[PDB]
Image (cartoon, coloured by chain):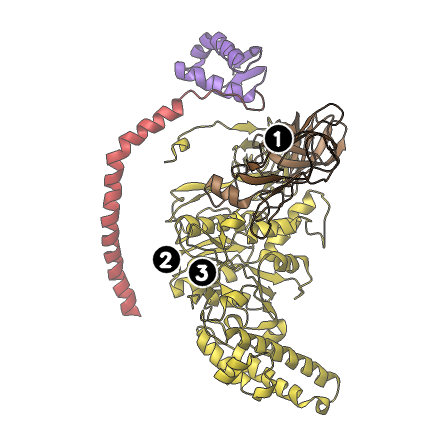
Chain colours: A brown, B yellow, C purple, D red
């Protein structure tokens, strides 16, 4: 939880940013602007803000999200229109009800208000599932008949529980992986 | 109802000034500096000048002074932090008034009785909320309308050089810009008083001061207000076109002068230059300016931006024309060779381009043959230029029959089709008929780029 | 008198400095001299810090 | 053209007469709602507005 030290165009230098990591998204300012740390020097982490940096003042809190620039992969992105970052332009227009893009808009990349039909894959409870394996399928469109749900890569273990067939949203749990005794909850995305 | 306007926020008058360097003023101790903040530098002489905070350190604030730093003391100068970005007062009555480079009245009239305070930088329009223009503007110039069409909502600049009649061409386009009335927002960035007087006189004679707003930043005006004038004019245009639902045609002139101002500010900041000293972020700044043109889904109203530009040495490869071609869609190339030959307008249709012509031209919008005729004209003009080069380098008899016919076409094209007197106002249909008359020089066989059905139906 | 109470405090909370120099009209000097203690206590309460060390009526 | 300028001079009186009609309401519109605006302006200039910077907290 550092503080803004310097602002000059997109490049923002934030002090007290100790323990940060390179190319880690950090919410700069009070509007929670997305920015990736591109340079570190001591406790100051140079950040490039992904939105309009005008109005940022020294002392504004900078929140470390702890993850790199991550794209939300899953059902629901097969038709939508995205900005540079995975910002849904249609969802932004619908929620904001305006022709502008509000600063620090936090609309989820994949909308969670749509119920997706899910058919579990060949994997069952107790089987060993590795990264990238298929444990389901989602009927997205007529063209994309089966949006096969992939277990995230570099995530592995044994299926503690798998959901039955039914209309599930992205926030809802789909499958559970135990690994080394630390059960992990995996959703549609 | 904007009831939040009734609020007083006292401002911090900093007498802590240092590092006054060129266009830049540096404040040693600032309590929570705000980036892109407007300050009011009160000189020891008593005159105030607005300034923009370019960068903030922990306690510093590198301020750029729009009116210049000539006379700024380090001891008696007080800098007052307003606390917000620059907000021009906009109104519907703001049409018909002449403004300074910093949005101050020049016509000896009152200050704008503000209807709202709009930020200069505006807001980023949702690309999903934009409309593809697809509405041709009958600019009345043959070399433009027929071969590089302008759609209502298209940012098409006029690339020109020093001494060419770019001002005359743009004034003509503004005077005669009906669709196949327009409000106008004119921004003068460093143009000489002769050019500003020409533009104002032409607007008044045509009857445009009823529905125009001039932001005149002359050459004698301070050289950093050229950074702010296009933004003020463009947010005025955004207001007039989106909230009052008008159709605005912005004529930002001497964007080369704007880029020179940018380079001057960039050079003073001692930052990584880029190409020819122009700031590396010149693409981003030019995109921020140019990309404020077009139509929006909810609101019927557009900014038909036509940013006049001046090539330093008639070179496209220069950073300003190159980036302007990258961002702004299309280009109207004013040719020194054509002007020397005496053609008006001296528009060279080979470099001139319009990305939205293929969609705003033809198929019942104007006429069935517009696109094919413009392709045929471009192809035969390129053939004529190549044949002229070949006939200069080698013997004339070595040129083929097609090459000789194309030389004749090029002569009859520059001298009759492109050549258009001021106030002529050729309709797009009349220009197409004249272009066909030029294309009837060739036998039907060699009009290869014309679709055979149209060739049979129009030859 | 209550209006001047906020005007001095409103600017004090913007400065946020341990010391102050309140330049006022010659007729409000007595009022500010009387109410310096209240101003200090209000600034200490509103700025979430210790009351400012000294206020000087210029 | 001189007659047009002379007519414009007559039109200047006509324009002034037209302007006098519009700005007659401007004086009337002001006085009708002047005392209400002053009440808002006075109450705002004096209103206690004491709040530190958000960053200072």
Q: Residue furthest bottom?
A: B397
Mark 1 highlights which residue?
B75
Left or right of residue B262: residue B83: left
| Element class at badge 2 | helix
Q: Residue A36 in the image: state x and y as whole percent.
A: 68, 37
**Residue A26 x %, y %:** 66, 32
Camera-nearest residue between B191 and B415 = B415
Labels 2 and 3 share a subunit: yes
Residues at discs 2 and 1 both on one chain: yes
User: Which residue position holds label 2?
Assistant: B210
Circle 2 or circle 3, nearest the eye: 2
Please name the residue shown 54% across and 63% down the image. Answer: B356
Near mark 3 (Cα within 10 A), the count class, few <14, some 14-19 or many ≥20, is: many
Foreground pick, B135 / B287 = B135
Residue placed under numbered mark 3 in the picture:
B200
Vertical side of B309 occupied by B261: above or below? above
**Crowding at mark 2 (Cα within 10 Å: few <14, some 14-19, many 20+):** some
Distance of label 2 from label 1 (alpha carbons): 47 Å
The location of residue B132, given as percent across then percent down, is 50, 58
Real-space CA distance between mark 1 and mark 3, rounded to the nearest whole angstrom: 42 Å
Q: Earlier in the sequence, mark 2 or mark 1?
A: 1
Q: Do the residues bearing badges 2 and 3 touch, measured as CB atoms within 8 Å?
A: no
Say above or below: B52 vs B430. above
Relative to B335, say whether B156 is above or below: above
**Residue at 75% in and 86% down:** B394
């Amino acid at each position: 939880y550092g503080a803004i030290y310097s602002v000059s165009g997109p490049v923002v230098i934030a002090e007290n940013m100790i323990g940060c990591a390179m190319y880690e998204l950090v919410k700069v300012g009070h509007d929670n602007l997305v920015g990736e740390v591109i340079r570190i020097d001591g406790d100051k982490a140079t950040i490039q803000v992904y939105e309009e940096t005008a109005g940022l003042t020294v002392g504004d809190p900078v929140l470390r999200t702890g993850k790199p620039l991550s794209v939300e992969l899953g059902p629901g992105l097969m038709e939508t229109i995205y900005d540079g970052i995975q910002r849904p332009l249609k969802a932004i227009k619908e929620e904001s009800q305006s022709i502008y893009i509000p600063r620090g808009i936090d609309t989820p990349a994949l909308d969670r208000t749509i119920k997706w039909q899910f058919t579990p894959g060949k994997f069952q409870v107790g089987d060993h599932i590795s990264g990238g394996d298929i444990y389901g399928s989602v009927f997205e469109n007529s063209l994309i008949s089966s949006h096969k749900i992939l277990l995230p890569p570099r995530s592995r273990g044994t299926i503690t529980w798998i959901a039955p067939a039914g209309e599930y949203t992205l926030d809802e749990k789909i499958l559970e992986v135990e690994f080394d005794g630390k059960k992990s909850d995996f959703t549609l995305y | 109802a904007v009831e939040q306007g009734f609020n007083v926020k006292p401002r911090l008058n900093y007498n802590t000034v240092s590092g006054v360097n060129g266009p830049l003023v540096i404040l040693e101790k600032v309590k929570f500096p705000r980036y892109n903040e407007i300050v009011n530098l009160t000189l020891p002489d008593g005159t105030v000048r607005q300034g923009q905070v370019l960068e903030i350190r922990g306690d510093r604030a590198i301020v750029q002074v729009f009116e210049g730093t000539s006379g700024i003391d380090v001891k008696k100068t007080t800098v007052e932090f307003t606390g917000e970005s620059l907000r021009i007062p906009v109104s519907e009555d703001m049409l018909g008034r002449i403004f300074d480079g910093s949005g101050r009245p020049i016509d000896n009239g009152p200050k704008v009785f503000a209807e709202d305070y709009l930020d200069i930088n505006g807001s980023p329009i949702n690309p999903y909320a934009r409309i593809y223009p697809e509405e041709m503007i009958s600019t009345g110039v043959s070399a433009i309308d027929t071969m590089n069409s302008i759609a209502r909502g298209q940012k098409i600049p006029i690339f020109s050089a020093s001494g060419l009649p770019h001002n005359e061409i743009a004034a003509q386009i503004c005077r005669q810009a009906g669709l196949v009335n327009f409000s106008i927002v004119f921004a003068a960035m460093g143009v000489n008083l002769e050019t500003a007087r020409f533009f104002k006189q032409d607007f008044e004679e045509n009857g445009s001061l009823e529905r125009t707003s001039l932001f005149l930043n002359l050459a004698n005006d301070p050289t950093i207000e050229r950074i702010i004038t296009p933004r003020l004019a463009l947010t005025t245009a955004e207001y007039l076109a989106y909230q009052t639902e008008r159709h605005v045609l912005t004529i930002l002139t001497d964007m080369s002068s704007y880029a020179d101002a940018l380079r001057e500010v960039s050079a003073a900041r001692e930052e990584v230059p880029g190409r020819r000293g122009y700031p590396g972020y010149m693409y981003t700044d030019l995109s921020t300016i140019y990309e404020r043109a077009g139509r929006v889904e909810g609101r019927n109203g557009s900014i038909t931006q036509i940013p006049i530009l001046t090539m330093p040495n008639d070179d496209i490869t220069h950073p300003i024309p190159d980036l302007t071609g990258y961002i702004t869609e299309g280009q109207i190339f004013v040719d020194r060779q054509l002007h020397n030959k005496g053609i008006y307008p001296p528009i060279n249709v080979l470099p001139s381009l319009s990305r939205l012509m293929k969609s705003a031209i033809g198929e019942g919008m104007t006429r069935k043959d517009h696109g094919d005729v413009s392709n045929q004209l471009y192809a035969k003009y390129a053939i004529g230029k190549d044949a002229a080069a070949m006939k200069a380098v080698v013997g004339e008899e070595a040129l083929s029959i097609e090459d000789k016919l194309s030389l004749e076409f090029l002569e009859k094209f520059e001298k009759t089709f492109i050549t258009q007197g001021a106030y002529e106002d050729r309709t797009v249909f009349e220009s197409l008929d004249q272009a066909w008359s030029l294309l009837r020089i060739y036998p039907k066989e060699m009009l290869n780029r014309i679709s055979p059905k149209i060739l049979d139906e129009f030859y | 008198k209550p209006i001047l109470q906020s005007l001095i405090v409103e600017a004090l909370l913007k400065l946020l400095e341990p010391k102050a120099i309140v330049k006022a009209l010659e007729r409000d000097v007595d009022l500010i001299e009387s109410m310096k203690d209240d101003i200090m206590r209000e600034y200490g309460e509103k700025a979430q810090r210790a009351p400012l060390e000294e206020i000087v009526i210029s | 053209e001189q007659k047009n300028a002379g007519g414009v001079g007559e039109l200047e009186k006509k324009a002034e007469a037209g302007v006098q009609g519009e700005l007659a309401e401007i004086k009337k519109i002001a006085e009708k709602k002047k005392d209400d605006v002053v009440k808002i302006l006075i109450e705002t200039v004096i209103k206690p507005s004491a709040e530190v910077h958000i960053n200072a907290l």
